[PDB]
Length: 601
Ligand code: NA
Image (cartoon, rainbow, N blue to C red; front, side, top):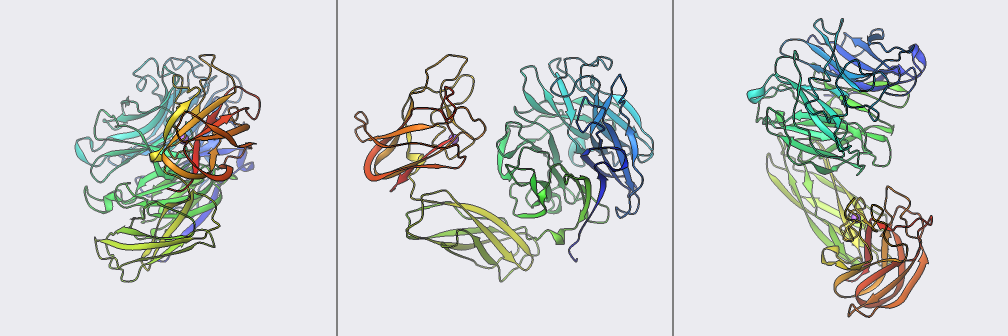
């Protein structure tokens, strides 16, 4: 109906007994009561600090909230005990409510020492509070032993927010709560902890990935369980894996590029929980997270209409500071969002009318052109339900002196639509890497995407490495070849330690894949490390590949995270070489995320 979005604070730092409140968890009890849990950090720090698990309750659907009650109290006096990071799981079949959390003594996540002995004050224990009266009273259990099938699981904690209960297939009824372990090899993984007997016993399934962290799982329209993870390896995205079973295992983990994430927690739920398998309502997902990849801000709610393959809908609920966010389906049709606005924990309620709309994911290919040219690219739209929209619009988002126009024929129920985008870029347009936003305006809601228009740069798919002085390829992937893949996240690294290799006169050459008229080169520093940054450099070109001529350019580039230009008077060359003479802070290695050659295709 009319678009709804309201919010109020449940916890405000300093008031009501704690200097810090953090780590949100939202649930709706079997009888319509909203339950919100979070840490009360007397220390403002997580485990092993004396944190307490708290709870506020709303019986009128979320408008008014009760007093702040303690679910698990931490001991500030020695010996220090703490409880942290709550996560609710509601067994819709029996009525039991489970609040999972970290139980700390002397060690936190990174300090936990091997062992399952509840008594050993050196392991981060896995606790569960159970309640049979809708959350009023609780029963605590330490299940660290039930869930540590491998003596190597040195550490663990339950990912905050809220767990699930399968509805479909042969495991309908199973409860699932996600964890993050630290295996024997020091690696962080994702593991599903589940119960087939309504929580009396909890067993752990098969672990997944490397560089995982707080992860979330959801039931797809077909019983498949999608897993959406924070990436501890900081690639600015969410990793995802899928499972098709009940003794839980997921396939390979890959990165979702439609999910920009600053390496933070995120929420993903079924928009219509009780929809039947296969139906269109069972295919609708809601995901909340911080859209910024460099910051914990720009809280945006995204919608998927095909089990998470496409994410056309999106809206910002908090443009400002936004860290952890957790979602829940309300019995009235709306959704409850409990998050961290920086002031403590806030509660929000919104409905789908407020999100924008139309499940019409669309695609527009990436375009490469020369400055001063006009290019027309096709648009492909894939339409949903009550969608006979005779008049849809296409609003592109680019640079002011760029003429961009687009059109799409009408949308017909469950049909594919066509259209096209005409881009015109001026002759004084500086070389490559341009993001263009497209927005499908319709009277039934929004749908948006982004494509790339690269100007005056050669094709990396035609490039190869002619030579390199050293490549770190044992301890890590510092391959010379990671410079030509279109990914800032991957980098070439000089043979670093764990082998005392050569010092600074470092270099790399690219085989352009034929003779081109080139007039420049752009390089992006390695993004998440500052000691293998190139300072002084010199460029050399060649066309026979053996006799190099130059330097055609020389300079010292900066500490800039964006691409930096090495310009020179146009010339023909089949290969280009970058000689790095020094590192910005005098350290011994060179690392390059990406190399771009400016020229004519
Ligand atoms: Na790269």
